[PDB]
Amino acid sequence: PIVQNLQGQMVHQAISPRTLNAWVKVVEEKAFSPEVIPMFSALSEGATPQDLNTMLNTVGGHQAAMQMLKETINEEAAEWDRLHPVHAGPIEPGQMREPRGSDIAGTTSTLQEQIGWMTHNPPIPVGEIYKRWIILGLNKIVRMYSPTSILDIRQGPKEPFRDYVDRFYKTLRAEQASQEVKNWMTETLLVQNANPDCKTILKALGPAATLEEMMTACQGVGGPGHKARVL
Amino acid sequence: PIVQNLQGQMVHQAISPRTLNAWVKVVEEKAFSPEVIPMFSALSEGATPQDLNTMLNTVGGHQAAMQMLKETINEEAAEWDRLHPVHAGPIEPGQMREPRGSDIAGTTSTLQEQIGWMTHNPPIPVGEIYKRWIILGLNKIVRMYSPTSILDIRQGPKEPFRDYVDRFYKTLRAEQASQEVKNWMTETLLVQNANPDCKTILKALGPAATLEEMMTACQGVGGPGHKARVL
Amino acid sequence: PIVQNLQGQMVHQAISPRTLNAWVKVVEEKAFSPEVIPMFSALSEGATPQDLNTMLNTVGGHQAAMQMLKETINEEAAEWDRLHPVHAGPIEPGQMREPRGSDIAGTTSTLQEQIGWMTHNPPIPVGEIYKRWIILGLNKIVRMYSPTSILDIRQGPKEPFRDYVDRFYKTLRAEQASQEVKNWMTETLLVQNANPDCKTILKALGPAATLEEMMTACQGVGGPGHKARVL
Amino acid sequence: PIVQNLQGQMVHQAISPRTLNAWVKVVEEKAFSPEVIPMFSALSEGATPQDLNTMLNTVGGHQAAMQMLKETINEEAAEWDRLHPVHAGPIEPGQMREPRGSDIAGTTSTLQEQIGWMTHNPPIPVGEIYKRWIILGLNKIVRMYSPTSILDIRQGPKEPFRDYVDRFYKTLRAEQASQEVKNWMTETLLVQNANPDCKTILKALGPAATLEEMMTACQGVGGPGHKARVL
Amino acid sequence: PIVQNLQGQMVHQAISPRTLNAWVKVVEEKAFSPEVIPMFSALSEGATPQDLNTMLNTVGGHQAAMQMLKETINEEAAEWDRLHPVHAGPIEPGQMREPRGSDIAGTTSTLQEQIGWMTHNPPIPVGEIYKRWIILGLNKIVRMYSPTSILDIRQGPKEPFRDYVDRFYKTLRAEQASQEVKNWMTETLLVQNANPDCKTILKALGPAATLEEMMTACQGVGGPGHKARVL
């Protein structure tokens, strides 16, 4: 990575053996899940592609999911060269040569070169871009690794509505639905697979049930006894 | 985060796992509550928009109240852009722009503009501006998940007033109410309702008693004496 | 009506048979209702008082209503003169004299006067100004036939709100009420006619609140709500 | 409307009464259907903010719905100006007329101002920016509730297999859906009376298989419905 | 449309509603046999993506068949952007950006871009390429909504040799197969599926008898001549 210490210029130095040991531990414990992913961003700060390959190469678990992540990388990069032209003139004074997708995976680029792009001013953000495409590569596994579908959701026989709204959102964390499909899921599919008596309170909102309306709903008399007031 | 420097002007440093684990720890003990608003604020020191979102993202549970934080973010970001008009034309050499709704919420947050707003003079804490909205939203989570009114304080038929007062004071943390308003509560309610051995202690204290004197009030009243032990 | 030339002098052209023919499809079908007027105003795009008199001449229908309309047009002319202090004022050599009401109506004036005023620098818009007296004359003859007005409208007992909001707006189209009176209706009779859940929010937020907040109300269930849990 | 595009200098004209009659005919029969947006888009080609305001002026049905489209216009013209620069002050680089939201709704602009903007080369797309908010006002009228959701569509045994599908695709004309929701319905509700031998065929085709491929399938298996033949 | 394309005269006219209606009538009655594609070609003379986009969306009915055609043209845009080389090194640009798959189908391209591909010298063929993607969509519809297959066309034991042919040809018009395959079906398969007395008559005619005589040949089936045939 790239680091600042007590120096005058940025220091290019390798990833820590401590940070790779912490990395494999979360992967042994947790596989790939949506909690893994901001764990991932925080240890890949100021990454070169060489630091990212080192994380990918240290993993010895999940061998089949990892080959699907490299097929996803090959695809985002392949989209990267089509969407942003790679024909150019000659390289002007002051400037460095320009990344294309195999440069962003670091397959064509070398280490001194990759570092040299990200210490340039404004930086050319070769690790940042490659990090984003591997979060997408994570997202594809994390989606398959989930223990249940979003479409099979329904409320526990005595589950509070609040805790089911919560659970439904938690299963919805890595889920790549559009804003209107996410709203139809919340206002239809969630409600429709609810308790009948909470469904009937919620019925009387009409069109456009909010999150603030959902939370405040179903607070009635009867049912379960209250928790004591001196705890 | 962005972190003060011995040998220069401010510098970036990556968000540690230890900081991650310590936020998620108080969530496991006591979740969204009055307690966890200064704990998240104690850990917010030097964080950017991205580190603060990284902090929210690493959390497994607690996700419908997080949906109401996202909802709350959505409310304030529209308000700040509605409040503050856009400048026409371009910003002068070595000056920085206004913080926009999308930048304080983190969607348009990039490091070099983060570092621009921290090397300006006065420096601009774009992370405190974001933090204020997140602890603004944690207040609303507390109100949404509240059982009933703050002025419902219960007591048992032989209690010596000490936990009863603490329970009042704990109950009132949801409010911002004056310390003189609380004392007045104590005169009008807590002293009034006291069990009669403790009530006899309280009555001879004087009606214009100070908060110090009320700490030594009912100390040793009733019970199987003292089961507490010196440490 | 007038046709713009970018290579030389303006062209003024008689009223077209297809303009008059489309006029006849409207006038003898929509007759004593407000539905003539916004289309008439559309046919009157870029019109001279002569063209408009020619569209009047093309109507053979409703002679005693058309005489009633002519009386309003005469009286509207008569009143343009009384809003004007100086009749036949001094004005520099080669421009167009200021128009009186009868000149605007087109019976003391020539076409070259009437195009003459329109094409002036600044424009004197006698075409639009006549049209405005005409459309006041059309609303009155709606209103002599059908005395239905914003103040008569009351909605049925099983009818919840949304049918009445249509009812108001369709009526308001040829309305004759004066500005203070129209405000009194929106603060008085709209609030009283409103059904209860909308009615409460109308008494709180006012009619200067958005129509949406009103239109989201009344889909709920009568009374103030079943009681929340016994704490 | 502004006419003469790609024929030198652009110049103004009047809105055609048979463009208006088709627009009125579109309101009478297809207001609640997404057919309105393309029709209005094309009918309003070349049309000024005033011609767009006349389009609204002309029409008489569904006023509560339509006034909520004016709330939509009021709200968007405010929302536009907090995204953009605004021409503010008497100063030299700020004093000039530039198109802020009220100009684009044509409330403070005259028609001549709007022609000037729109007859520029490249034009300044004032009637288009306003038209996008007319389209949102309509999209919100379309997006009003419709009896029959995609779950209120399932196979029955007395028709071709194809016509039940064809209805599912009518339902999803204004209703929003994911590919996973659509794939769930060929596991759930659109395969209810599907043949034993054919369910495997349909399932073997799976998520990847096209609509072509699903609606060709089953010529060997099952009764008359599967081969597209009447009961 | 933009018309007068061939001689570079490029004049813009917005679409009539009579041509959109003309289109839904073509979809509604002329799309299950290949008369839709020449009527469409003429109707799409000078059509821009905006124009063709407007026509696809205003069909309203015919949803499954539309969906199959959408999926067809969405497959063409994937293919288009897969097809092209990624060009690198020196390129001299010239006027007008590379239109991608989505640009071609109007979805990432504005009418003002569309006016660029049309105004270019030679005009760049984006509306032309999109119109024949739609004809790929309409070919699979002729196929899908076919009543019979060419092999199962057989002479009726009460049908004329001329009627048998007339139906065998028109089937053959709408069979998808390549031009030699259809030469083979004219030359061999036609003669194959004719009833024996007619096949026996055919031998007897040989090369000797001309094509007109065949139209009058094998009579006395269905009853006397050919017209009084039993139904």
Image: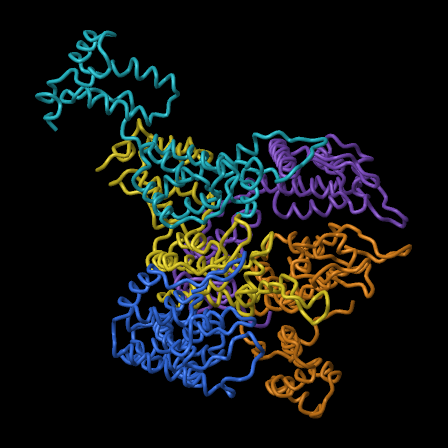
Chain colours: A purple, B orange, C blue, D yellow, E cyan
Query: Residue A69 in the image: x percent, y percent?
Result: 62, 35
* Whether residue A155 can be seen here: no
Query: Residue B104 in the image: x percent, y percent?
Result: 68, 60
In the image, farthest residue toward the front: C93
Residue drawn at (65%, 56%) of the image: B56
Residue A143 drawn above or below residue D107: above
Q: Residue C140, located in which quarter of the rendered image?
A: bottom left
- The image quadrant where one finds the N terminus of chain C is bottom left
Residue B114 drawn above or below residue D225: below
Q: Residue C146, located in which quarter of the rendered image?
A: bottom left
Q: Please name whichever residue, D146 or D120, is drawn nearer the observer in this view of the structure.
A: D120
* Whether residue B14 can be seen here: yes
Query: Residue A124 in the image: x percent, y percent?
Result: 76, 43
Query: Residue E5 in the image: x percent, y percent?
Result: 49, 38
Q: Please name whichever residue, E74 or D183, is drawn nearer the observer in this view of the structure.
A: E74
Q: Please name whichever residue, E142 or D142, is drawn nearer the observer in this view of the structure.
A: E142
Image label count: 0
Left or right: where does residue E40 sit relative to residue E75?
left
Residue A177 drawn above or below residue D130: above
Q: Please name whichever residue, E203 or A125, is drawn nearer the observer in this view of the structure.
A: E203
Q: Residue C159, located in which quarter of the rendered image?
A: bottom left
Residue drawn at (73%, 38%) of the image: A52
Left or right: where does residue B72 sit relative to residue D202?
right
Left or right: where does residue C66 sit relative to residue D171?
left
In the image, farthest residue toward the left: E224
Residue drawn at (67%, 36%) of the image: E93
